[PDB]
Image (cartoon, rainbow over all chains, first blue to last red; front, side, top):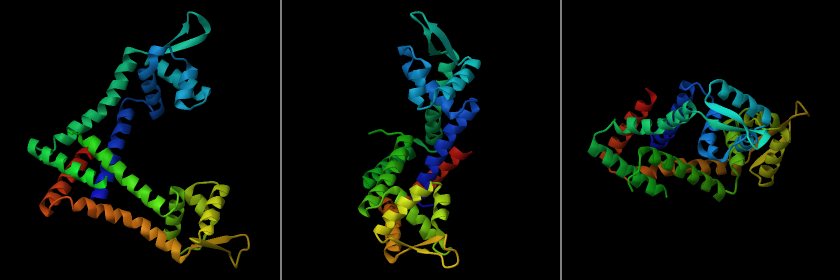
Length: 137
Length: 140
């Protein structure tokens, strides 16, 4: 195996593992992005229109998506007390936990990788990979 | 200066993609033009039409039309009306189109040799085996 092959395959498998984590948590990639956006910005009092612009999606796709997430109670929605025509959206406890669980896949892969080798071996491996990265730069 | 494997693999992949993009820039072709030339290169035997290229690239007719006009203006391809069917235009690479594709592709061998030359024979054997073990751990 050339390095080009190994690095390409490793990259591919890591991306696949992230997709599989979503599958295991029973959410689509777009639902994951929606939850992730709420996780980063819900302090602001976010509406469907905010979400729609963030996902670069139309209102109807956002509505179904929010309906799906709400049916699972990963999010909640309430009418804004000062604007009856507006509904704000927050993450529930379960929604926060799901986002953090998906995110944890990266740390989990890193630990899988590290556990393949002994401590000194990891040090040499990382040093040599750094030399390799340097040579491409 | 104490990076994760994840950071390192992502960065190495990023730099190899950037080197390939820089090779395209050096040859004065866009990514999409390179894909078009590469497809022609792989199917130099069939007598490909604009429609074949469109179906392969999954782009629209107009998009492929503009791409082919640009490549033809650079004389990297030629186009001619099929003798048996006047409704078909066939496309082939010129000498230079072939040379440009092979010049582009050379970047991958070049990077491989750059990477290998950073380590001794023994280190390389160890690195490859270890990367192989790591890849396997991500699969199972």
